Image (cartoon, coloured by chain):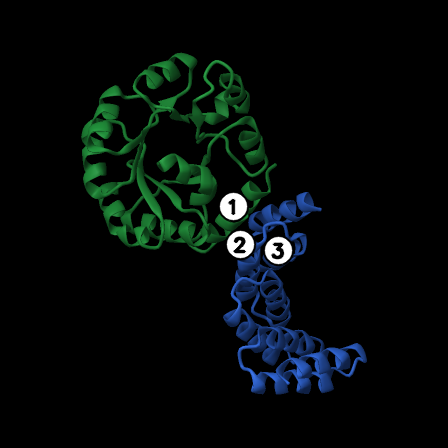
Amino acid sequence: SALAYVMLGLLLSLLNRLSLAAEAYKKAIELDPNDALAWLLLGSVLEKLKRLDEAAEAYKKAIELKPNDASAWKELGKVLEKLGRLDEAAKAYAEAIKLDPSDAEAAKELGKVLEKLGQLELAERAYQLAIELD
Amino acid sequence: KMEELFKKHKIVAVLRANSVEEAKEKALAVFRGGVHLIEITFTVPDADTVIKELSFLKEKGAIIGAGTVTSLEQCQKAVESGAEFIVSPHLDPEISKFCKINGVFYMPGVMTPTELVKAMKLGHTILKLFPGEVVGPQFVKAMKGPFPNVKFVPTGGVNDQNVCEWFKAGVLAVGVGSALVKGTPEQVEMLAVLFVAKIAGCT
């Protein structure tokens, strides 16, 4: 039943009933607290539900399970950038590039965070990395 | 050997600071940024104490060594401090004998073909190309013919715009110093993860 509720949340996410999908992922979490897919999907659903403070907590719980997901770190960078922790998001985008230096999106989004944070030289070096990848 | 460790991490942090506490901060940021080869130059006052105070990073998987060694008596304090490799900007034959007997890896400074031959006769096949901003990657690609065994780790003129030119020429690693040293102890960690990414992306 742990997997079935995850498939239920995926189906509900296809019908834009996101709040109903979040309840499905949470039920699979109660059944198995170590299901990293349930945590990662819950973070991406709450991100679109704009529960950004709760969304980052599920993304951190997903990274705590599988600490080598460039998708989870990059998605945590989107939430923390929209939430307001620009320096904590740049540290999250950094861990995403440590795992995959070919992620053209993570390098482009890190240059945007650094450009708003101050260091144009650190941002420019990140912009050129993303441009060379694609 | 140390060569296989140079071939893996492919980057050496030529750390130059002013105080002892300033050096320990930048070494922590560089290691957190993914760079495991840290070259602590002896121009830093009391560099033999910085190397022995960073001994805990050798458990975390860091290779701390002493760089810019002018005299052999300076290499005495370098080996006794706990450095795992000795680096000099010039070729000093008496330092090579001391590092061979004590069992420490030594990378001399070479700029000419004759300085390379004299360093090869001492048994060295891994030389430091100082200053790389004068010889250029064309030098490394030129010595690939007559000396197919020498492996260069340049120090000068190695920036992010041409870091792939050095590697595609035939270098073993690169020693970035000015780019990694400049910045706050949090900008230094970010500068490392950006430099490690470009090296991994080179063809």
Residue mark closest to the camera, 1 vs 3: 1
Marks 1 and 3: CB-CB under 8 Å?
no
- Image quarter of residue B2: top left
Amino acid type at mark 1: Val
Q: In this view, does B74 lie above or below A122?
A: above
Amino acid type at mark 3: Glu
Q: Where is residue A40 in the image (x, y as percent from the top left)?
A: 62, 73
3D distance between C-alphas at marks 1 and 3: 20 Å
Say which chain is green: B
Q: In this view, does B56 lie above or below B96?
A: below
Q: Position of residue A51 (x, y in %)?
A: 65, 81
Q: Disc 2 is attached to a residue of which chain? A: A
Asked whether A11 or A51 is in front, the reply is A11
Residue lying at 67% horizontally and 43% vertically, measured from the top left: A132
- Image quarter of residue B175: top left
Disc 1 with disc 2 on a shared chain: no
Asked whether B137 or B47 is in front, the reply is B137
3D distance between C-alphas at marks 1 and 2: 8 Å
**Residue A115, numbered label:** 3
